[PDB]
Each structure stands twice: as C-alpha cells, then as structure tokens.
Length: 104
Image (cartoon, rainbow, N blue to C red; front, side, top):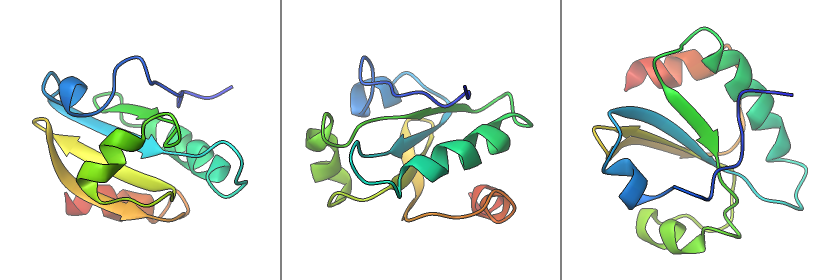
C-alpha cells in the first residue's frame, strides 16, 4: 500500500485546468524501472499534504505524451496553476527529489 495510485479517470490538460498545485508520474506496466518511483513519491508526499500526487499508465494515456514530447519513459511532470512548471525522465532517491521540487 502507498498514497500514489494510477489515475486515468481524470488526467491531462482537462484535469490540469482545474488544479492549483499537482504532480503526475507517467509510469509503464511491463518495465520494472518505473515501479520504484512510486515508493519515492509516497515518502515525498507523506510530509507535503498540500500537493496532489498521482501516477498514470503512459500506454493508456499516449495522447498526452504527444503534447509534452515524451517517448515511453518514467517521466515526472509537475503542474502549477494548470501549467507544466517542471519535468524530468528517469529515477531518483527521495533525498534528492526534495531539491527538484524546491527548484520549482
């Protein structure tokens, strides 16, 4: 169990138009690599109640990835005022993810 769950039911620009401060993780089904970042985001969100964090299957949501320029990779996307304010593809530890968020 963790606070980071797959949401396809509302995601992308039409959900971003409603939000003030949020984070979306574009994970994949097969690849073991994506599965780690959920545990990182859980520990990151546990001490930050005021940000809306979720994940989303990039193989179910490929029409969005076309607009941000993503290929097939574990991408963290950060939304402020409904605008993409910060973005990166890959994995990191929860110590260093604090500086990534602080940079925004």
